[PDB]
Image (cartoon, rainbow, N blue to C red):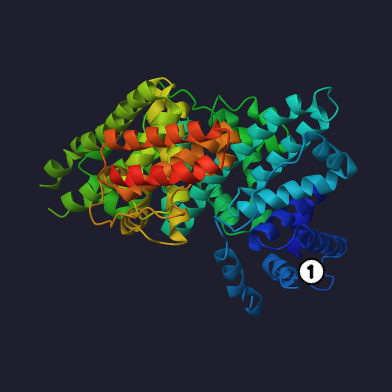
Amino acid sequence: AHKSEVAHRFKDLGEENFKALVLIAFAQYLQQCPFEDHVKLVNEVTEFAKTCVADESAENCDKSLHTLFGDKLCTVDCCAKQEPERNECFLQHKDDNPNLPRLVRPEVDVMCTAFHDNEETFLKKYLYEIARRHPYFYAPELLFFAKRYKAAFTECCQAADKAACLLPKLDELRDEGKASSAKQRLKCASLQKFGERAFKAWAVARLSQRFPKAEFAEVSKLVTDLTKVHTECCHGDLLECADDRADLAKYICENQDSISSKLKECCEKPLLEKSHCIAEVENDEMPADLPSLAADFVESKDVCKNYAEAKDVFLGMFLYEYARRHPDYSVVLLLRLAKTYETTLEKCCAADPHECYAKVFDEFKPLVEEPQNLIKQNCELFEQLGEYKFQNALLVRYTKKVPQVSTPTLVEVSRNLGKVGSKCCKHPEAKRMPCAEDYLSVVLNQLCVLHEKTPVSDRVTKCCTESLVNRRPCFSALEVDETYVPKEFNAETFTFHADICTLSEKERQIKKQTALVELVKHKPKATKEQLKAVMDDFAAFVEKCCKADDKETCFAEEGKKLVAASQAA
């Protein structure tokens, strides 16, 4: 009996997780609102929520969570709209690249002092700042990040060397957070742009790979519940999303016996760690005697009838049975193979159907080989180059493909592309295609959503809108764009300053990679040798001025000589 929905979620979630998730919701709905205004609205909804728990029939306790949350957000556009369209307004204002200050961390002493001052406020500020910069962050998972963040401060602020303790695990939480955010961003793009059916296929493939002993009926139930959780989170219904995720972890842990032998120690963890664990569990071992797919899906005389009479269950079963047998294939490849199976059946069943669809698996061969070769070639390139130089190679390659894309986006995307080598090439080859290609889908989706805000490349739009599961081959097949009009060297392109001499290795790299993008934009048809000449000359230029007696003056004078020697080469 859910008479009051805010009381229902408050009871299910507990006060602490309830008010954290309301804060996340508000910061993702209005990314530009100051922290103090948000905390004020959160405390008010929490106090009102308590009245509802005290009396579900009290005034306004029957209101939808959107009506209640939107009303408080509108106490500080969308606010002129009624609550079927007001929520859609808020959601659609979400900004993947908000114009917000770069979050710089102060000295370790200053942080530990602010933490000891008010631990609750310190943690709220962490939630607020991450959620406003990542408006699709998987909300229950952000609660896990905040728990680990607090634990790092609790422990390390009482150590002898507080920075030697604290900073490595903050940096790990920061990097892990941006990876988690990108992964969830792909789920939200899948659901919002390509619909529930696309996400459900994705979930069937992913869960069948991980839980290959599970029966189809079990996988389907898990897929239905998982789709509901992410539909809610991606639609900003964060309290429901977190509640249903906990129910799902509970269901899975109550049914390990029929799902996976690998869930044993995930299901012993506390609430948040348990759900985090299940979502990252290693694939279970597949059952030993699995029959060839050919019998039921290729060589039965009933394929066309079953495909016509029971299309969704039939193709779902095909994907389940194919994916559970192929932990070595990427998820997007399995979805490609499922689409190919479906299209071949549509053609064959309308034409000797039995002879036609007897050869369906023969079309899978080129689809399987293309990613295998892509990964083999790039992993050996990564072997001889290393992460940084591999990034440089991909940066040039992708700038040539889509030169209209903004330089910061090209730099961030390509650096993330390069990290696939350190992430996946080291793995044994069996796990290497799912590692590499499913991570590429996350990073290309970052390109898609960063570009969608300010569209400039027709080919990016084309690859991003045509077909989710074909995106990576789409981008891989692009060659150098001959229609781009090259950029002229201007003042913003170059002219370097003495601040470059003391940057972190990471910021030094980013600034050199930024310059690399710009001179590719200047001559998109430049060969590797020409790019290397100009970049070594820029390198020679940065070392001379950094160690000159008079920095900033060297940078101004030789900086003009550099752009002159670059536009000449």
Pinpoint residue 75: horizontal percent, then vertical percent.
76, 73
Pinpoint residue 436: horizontal percent, then vertical percent.
41, 33
Q: Depth check: 169 or 222 in front?
A: 169
**Residue at 38% across, 35% down:** 537
Q: Depth check: 559 or 212 in front?
A: 559
Farthest residue to the left: give it.
352
In the picture, measured across the screen, residue 112 lies left or right of residue 554, that is right
In the image, residue 21 sits, relative to residue 394, either above or below, namely below
**Residue at 84% across, 22% down:** 160
Query: How dense is the environment of label 1, judged by Cα within 10 Å: few (below 14), some, or many (20 and up)?
Result: many
Pinpoint residue 46: horizontal percent, then vertical percent.
82, 59
Residue 157, can we see it?
yes
Q: Secondary structure at mark 1?
A: loop
In the picture, measured across the screen, residue 143 lies left or right of residue 492, that is right
**Residue at 66% across, 52% down:** 131
**Residue at 30% across, 27% down:** 377
Q: Which residue in the protein does label 1 denote?
A: 61
Q: How many marks?
A: 1
Q: Amino acid at mark 1?
A: Cys
In the picture, measured across the screen, residue 50 lies left or right of residue 124, that is right
In the image, residue 98 sits, relative to residue 217, either above or below, namely below
In the image, residue 369 sits, relative to residue 399, either above or below, namely above
Residue 411, can we see it?
no
In the picture, measured across the screen, residue 346 lies left or right of residue 265, that is left
Name the quadrant of the N terminus.
Answer: bottom right
Pinpoint residue 303: horizontal percent, then vertical percent.
24, 45
Name the quadrant of the C terminus.
Answer: top left
